Image (cartoon, rainbow, N blue to C red):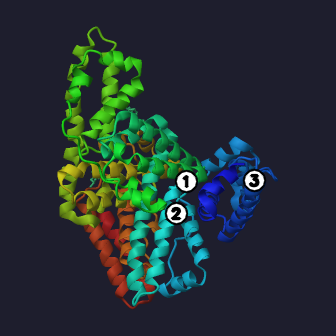
């Protein structure tokens, strides 16, 4: 029995949690009650297997079991139409079908949070259902959230309430902690979406290069054969979490943490604090540990990689291991480099060895490869310096606005909502990275852009409208940012023709938060630019200025939200004039 294997390892709590998250990520539209019901039924079954390891179907794989359970409500096409088909499938195909139907943008209603007085009551009255409800809302809206990690957020979420609801000012104690969690949750979800995308679209070889490079930066004192071992397990974990095998993902992740702690002295010195605390807190700790200090006397890479004469010979022998070694060596002494840059260099090396080793005199051909790295390191450096200077002048809001015009000009086909989301996030990278010293500025920025640009790529993959987006998303993972940076403005785009409804602002806007307000303007600026691509960064302002005048006035005037209808047609006339 497999269900039995996992149950024993994870226990009742975690087991139940993980299964709920899995079900939530599968049928995102299904209601809470139904998921709970299925989890229990499933958890009951599990219990019998622990005792009689062959009872009913205890001999099955989690796929068949999980699959059949969900298919007891999936067949209801009137609710989940396209799903029924999936249930008509079998074992492998049935599971792939489900994985294929996960929505990265579920049409679920926003998730507002009741007053502090209600949450605390609900929490205190029934603490279990409360927490379960949380896992459910998150899991269904983030179908790729790193499962083991969501259990850690669940614990911290519980501690927030467990303490604040006993305060003097609950609102003052809770709200902050919730905000900090809401964010970190999105960040966490984003990073994980990139990892799954990597494995799923580009293959495991790329996820490995990534793992080698980043682990090598954190553990410089570790030996290549040690890292490689770590890279192998780490890869197995995420492959599992990203395919939906959550229970085993949770298991393997635990084992890895165990190992890493035992062989502490062989790996890192800063692992001291991580191995002294609870499991969930230990895993989270390790995964977020600071790089160990760089080993004193280290020979130059040139020795074994560009000057030696056996280069091509060793390559041919075991190319992946040789490249793996190159990366490990280059990374361990370059934490001032972002993971994607390291992989870009590694790829420049591979391409050169491939060309150079088939020549009449290799050593002469591949002798100046490091000359080819100079541009690659410098390009990101200049880009960050220029954009951070701008960010430091305009501020976040205006800087996001600048990026909005820029992106809408590059990929006008893309849906207004998607562009607003991606442009806002891109702008948030300046608040995050620009404040650092040059030493930590590029790794921060470039690796973060890799997360944001992936968001666009997946959202776009749903309903493709721009071949320039498709191209820059599919041609090379590591080069996405460069590809997008090269795009200027789409010369083939044919301007949109005004639509009354799109530029009509209603009074229902005078009730929204300051945020949803600027987001309204931002959605207009985008619509504007789609109508007048050729327009310039000069004029737009003038109009955008006017846009504000409309809401302030029309909102503050006691005229029945009618100015909205009449003055709505007014602004349209001025614009067209410019
Ligand atoms: C990291 C951030 C602060 C600066 C930043 C943001 C987006 C871009 C892309 C390539 C663009 O401008 O299209 C470059 C630099
Ligand atoms: C293993 C490494 C040395 C070479 C390597 C690394 C990443 C990629 C991905 C798909 C890319 O090009 O974005 C290809 C080849």
Residue matched to label 2: 151
**First in sequence: mark 2 vs mark 1:** 2
- Say few, some or many: other residues with alpha carbon within 10 Å of mark 3 (under 14 / 14 to 19 / 20 or more): some
Quickly name the residue at label 3.
Answer: 68
282 vs 4, left or right, is left
In the drawing, does residue 151 fall left or right of residue 24?
left
Q: Pick the residue in front: 536 or 199.
A: 199
Give the side of residue 65 with respect to residue 320, left or right: right
Q: Is mark 2 within 8 Å of ligand 2?
A: no
Task: Give the vertical position of 122 relative to 70 (above or below).
Answer: below
x and y, in percent, of residue 69 in the image: 74, 57
Which of marks 3 and 1 precedes in the sequence? 3
Is 86 or 498 nearer to us in this picture?
86
In this view of the protein, can residue 538 be seen by the observer? yes
- Label pair 2/1, CB-CB below 8 angstroms: yes
- Secondary structure of the residue carrying tag 2 is helix
Identity of the residue furthest to the right in this view: 56
Task: Give the spatial CA distance, label 1 vs label 3.
Answer: 22 Å
- Circle 1 sits in a helix, a strand or a loop, which is it? helix
**What is the x, y in percent for residue 338?**
29, 45
Q: Earlier in the sequence, mark 3 or mark 2?
A: 3
Horizontal and vertical percent for residue 459?
Answer: 49, 52
Circle 1 sits on which residue? 250
In this rendering, position of residue 16 left or right of residue 229: right
Q: Residues within 10 Å of mark 1 (few under 14, many from 20)?
A: many
Q: Is residue 233 above or below residue 65?
A: above
């Amino acid at each position: 029995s497999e269900v039995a294997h996992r149950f024993k390892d994870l226990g009742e709590e975690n087991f139940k949690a993980l299964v709920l998250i899995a079900f939530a990520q599968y049928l995102q539209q299904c209601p809470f009650e139904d998921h709970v019901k299925l989890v229990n039924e499933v958890t009951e079954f599990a219990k019998t297997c622990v005792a009689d390891e062959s009872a009913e179907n205890c001999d099955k794989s989690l796929h068949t079991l999980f699959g059949d359970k969900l298919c007891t409500v999936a067949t209801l096409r009137e609710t989940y139409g396209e799903m029924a088909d999936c249930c008509a499938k079998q074992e492998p195909e049935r599971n792939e079908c489900f994985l294929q139907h996960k929505d990265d943008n579920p049409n679920l209603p926003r998730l507002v949070r009741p007053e502090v007085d209600v949450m605390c009551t609900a929490f205190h009255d029934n603490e279990e259902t409360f927490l379960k409800k949380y896992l459910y809302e998150i899991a269904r809206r983030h179908p790729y959230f790193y499962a083991p990690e969501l259990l850690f957020f669940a614990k911290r979420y519980k501690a927030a309430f467990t303490e604040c609801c006993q305060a003097a000012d609950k609102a003052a104690c809770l709200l902050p902690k919730l905000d900090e969690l809401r964010d970190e949750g999105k960040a966490s979800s984003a990073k994980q979406r990139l990892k799954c995308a990597s494995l799923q679209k580009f293959g495991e070889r790329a996820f490995k290069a990534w793992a080698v490079a980043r682990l090598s930066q954190r553990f410089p004192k570790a030996e290549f054969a040690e890292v490689s071992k770590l890279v192998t397990d780490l890869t197995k974990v995420h492959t599992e979490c990203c395919h939906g095998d959550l229970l085993e993902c949770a298991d393997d992740r635990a084992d890895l943490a165990k190992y890493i702690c035992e062989n502490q002295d062989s790996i890192s010195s800063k692992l001291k604090e991580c191995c002294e605390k609870p499991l969930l807190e230990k895993s989270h700790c390790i995964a977020e540990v600071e790089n160990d200090e760089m080993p004193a006397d280290l020979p130059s890479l040139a020795a074994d990689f560009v000057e030696s004469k056996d280069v091509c010979k060793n390559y041919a022998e075991a190319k992946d291991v040789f490249l793996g070694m190159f990366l490990y060596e280059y990374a361990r002494r370059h934490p001032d480099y972002s993971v994607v840059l390291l992989l870009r260099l590694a790829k420049t090396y591979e391409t050169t060895l491939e060309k150079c080793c088939a020549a009449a005199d290799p050593h002469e051909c591949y002798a100046k490869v490091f000359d080819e790295f100079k541009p690659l390191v410098e390009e990101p450096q200049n880009l960050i310096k220029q954009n951070c200077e701008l960010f430091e002048q305009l501020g976040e809001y205006k800087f996001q606005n600048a990026l909005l015009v820029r992106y809408t000009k590059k990929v006008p086909q893309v849906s207004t909502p998607t562009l607003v989301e991606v442009s806002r996030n891109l702008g948030k990278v300046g608040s995050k990275c620009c404040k650092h010293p040059e030493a930590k500025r590029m790794p921060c920025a470039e690796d973060y852009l890799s997360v944001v640009l992936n968001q666009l790529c997946v959202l776009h993959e749903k309903t493709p409208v721009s071949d320039r987006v498709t191209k820059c998303c599919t041609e090379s993972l590591v080069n996405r940012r460069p590809c997008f940076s090269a795009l200027e403005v789409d010369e083939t785009y044919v301007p949109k023709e005004f639509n009354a409804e799109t530029f009509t602002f209603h009074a229902d806007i005078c009730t929204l938060s300051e945020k949803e307000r600027q987001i309204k303007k931002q959605t207009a600026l985008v619509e504007l630019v789609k109508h007048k691509p050729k327009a310039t960064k000069e004029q737009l302002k003038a109009v955008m200025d006017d846009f504000a005048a409309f809401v302030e006035k029309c909102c503050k005037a006691d005229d029945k939200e009618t100015c909205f209808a009449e003055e709505g047609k007014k602004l349209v006339a001025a614009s067209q004039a410019a």
